[PDB]
Amino acid sequence: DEDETTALVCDNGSGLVKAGFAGDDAPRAVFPSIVGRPRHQGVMVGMGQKDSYVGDEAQSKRGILTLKYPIEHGIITNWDDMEKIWHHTFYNELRVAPEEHPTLLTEAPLNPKANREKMTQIMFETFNVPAMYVAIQAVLSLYASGRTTGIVLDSGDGVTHNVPIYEGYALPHAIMRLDLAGRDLTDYLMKILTERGYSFVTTAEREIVRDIKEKLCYVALDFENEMATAASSSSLEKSYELPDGQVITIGNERFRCPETLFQPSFIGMESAGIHETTYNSIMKCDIDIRKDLYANNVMSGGTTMYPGIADRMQKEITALAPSTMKIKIIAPPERKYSVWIGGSILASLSTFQQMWITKQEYDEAGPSIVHRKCF
Amino acid sequence: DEDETTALVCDNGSGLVKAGFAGDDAPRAVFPSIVGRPRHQGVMVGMGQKDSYVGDEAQSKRGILTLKYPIEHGIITNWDDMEKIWHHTFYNELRVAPEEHPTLLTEAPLNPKANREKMTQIMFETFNVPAMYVAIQAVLSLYASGRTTGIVLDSGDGVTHNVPIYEGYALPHAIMRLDLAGRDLTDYLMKILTERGYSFVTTAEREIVRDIKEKLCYVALDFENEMATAASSSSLEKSYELPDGQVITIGNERFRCPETLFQPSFIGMESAGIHETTYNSIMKCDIDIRKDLYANNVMSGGTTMYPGIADRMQKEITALAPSTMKIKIIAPPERKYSVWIGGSILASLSTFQQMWITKQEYDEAGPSIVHRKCF
Amino acid sequence: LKLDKENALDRAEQAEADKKAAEDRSKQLEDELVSLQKKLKGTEDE
């Protein structure tokens, strides 16, 4: 339905896919990274029932479906399901497809090599894209934030990367890969809500919990004070209506789940916590770099939407950082949608038009070309 | 009749409850977790007729009683009925009044908190027990089974908990609680027997089916080949005599019902099955842990009593498992009675005499005390 | 019949007692076998 001869952009994780076309400042639509399948045998005639559901179809009908997510902590392994997700995304809902447009897909800086190779290959071989470019989420996070310099706290669905860039250059030894993201926070909340008498086991139930979390949970500027009160009084509880007519209230659990980011030990993870990983991405860089990264701590990805996170991360780093120097967190409304936006910026910059793999070079070289042309 | 203030121990499941005193190796008495109520008025003289029936009384007169189980998927929701069960259990069959003896009760690691609070509160406020301690079923399973390390599959009536333990420590990031249990197998068997012409729809009938299941059913080491044979020949059928003199036989139904453990979709549950659930508990654990958990897969609770479950589970995990690793299932005669036995072991350990909540600490703190004192 | 529940029960109990001694041996032997096999593989790997 679109007639603008621009690039297309998609951010694909273990939870959601943000997508739209390059040159704008927002995705046109956001789809779940889901291929749904019926988990029941139909009995009655005229009950519909699809063999497969894609994206929002899968999420909307989830009460009777098993929901599969193709991306594992940042890597696409089920490329067949991503092809279905991308077809729906582009052809059915965004109303624009790669066949007539160059396409940019994103990944984390240390994401296994197979991910960028398959993203490049599927757009060229199943979507017939005229050109490709696999982007680094850290690059996109700073473009969308108005920075060339800063720490990218790309807290996604399956992984948080924690990666510094200075004057446009990577500082890779200072990357603190962390196995804690929005999907793990959802799983933890399912377990602590089970402790409250509301067990959540199935994937439809996981989606209910993700909705509860996104609307009711927060990290808190001061965890212990919120905890002591919330664990002692109903005045700190918030109600949510479950899609069966039950009402669930959440007290200190409302923040204990989100707290996992600062205390990963809550889910059995071996990690110093998001504020120390942020601190180390700054501290492991050279001393004439450190000061600029402290002043430019940039949030991207989701989980950045928890109340108290932009104020808390600044508090936790300034408390570890030396005095006089100003420590600042950048946390715009483009929060969680900023990686897509950065993709739009990179794809459309004139300074990037020589970075695209055309369907010339790709056909002669094959998918290994991504390591010659992208990064 | 005891010459020491030994703790009394009660393993109260959603199905059956086992009881005895600490220091024994078996419960002294077993009761269903049932309080029965008549739905009919008796006519004949000399027919008993009570307002309510407890434990074995509910089963003996069940033909006209509604049988209520006060425990729902591991949690007591009806505390009045548990008081009837505990009075009868401790006072009439164990012959001990709790007033002069400490009491140990059990719950799953993710059992809703209100369960531990009521178990503790009832014994302190209604029975005046001098002390209380709510045990972890995973611990008790390991102490009865002779292990400190392994996978605990406690396959109870209301829930299969599924928790890996290493060197006496929980590995909570790998708990995969499953809402598929012995109660669903009984309900499914009532329905599959109905398909064969033997309808079971009442509470009395539920108990009849429960007895049929326990004596006639098995999982089969190869479902499809056993099914094809059972569906083709009477050689795999087994008879049972019903209370009214009718005879029921079970064919491939004999395993199609138990198969629900491996295929939960049969009862409408979204799950990969007990063997993938078990496997999910062994691979998610750390690289230097996995080998010890594979070699120590521990069964406790009932359903573990199906003739082919220890061998099929060992086979399924072996099939999912990497090579080199030794896969072994421990399926002791203390099966279904293991949690109670572990309770006896725990209550009497010298290392556990400081873990008891006294009826001093309890009254000063209130029912929530169990949260900080037990686990 | 008069003493047959007793003969059968004594057989059941004696068989259960022997079964258990032998089942406990089976578990002990299996655990030793598996550990021994792991020692075997330990040494075979070596």
Image (cartoon, coloured by chain):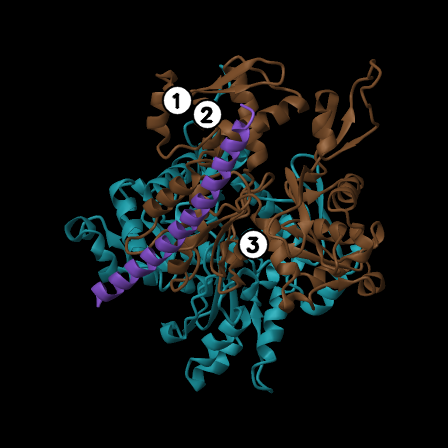
Chain colours: A cyan, B brown, C purple
Identify which residue is drawn at 71% across, 27% down: B60
Foreground disc of the pair 1, 2: 1
Residue B254 is tagged as 2
Instruction: Name the element at disc 3.
Output: helix
Residue B236 is tagged as 1
- In this orientation, which residue lies closer to the viewer: A249 or A16? A249
Comes first in the chain, label 1 or label 2: 1
Residue C4 is tagged as none
Give the image location of residue A213, x and y in percent: 62, 51
Residue wearing tag 3: B138
C-alpha span from label 3 to label 2? 30 Å
Above or below, A191 relative to B348: above
Instruction: Name the element at disc 2.
Output: helix
Using the rendered view, name the quadrant where residue B205 is placed. Answer: top right
> Chain ID for label 1?
B
- Cβ atoms at labels 1 and 2 below 8 Å apart: yes
Give the image location of residue B118, x and y in percent: 76, 50
Give the image location of residue C30, x and y in percent: 35, 53
Residue type of the residue flagged with mark 2: Arg
- Cβ atoms at labels 3 and 2 below 8 Å apart: no
Crowding near pointer 3: few (<14 within 10 Å), some, many (20+)? many
- In this orientation, which residue lies closer to the viewer: A324 or A51? A51
C-alpha span from label 1 to label 2? 9 Å
> Chain ID for label 2?
B
Identify which residue is drawn at 64% across, 47% down: B27
- In this orientation, which residue lies closer to the viewer: B172 or A147? B172
Residue type of the residue flagged with mark 1: Leu
Comes first in the chain, label 3 or label 2: 3
Comes first in the chain, label 3 or label 1: 3
Q: Are marks 3 and 1 on the same chain?
A: yes
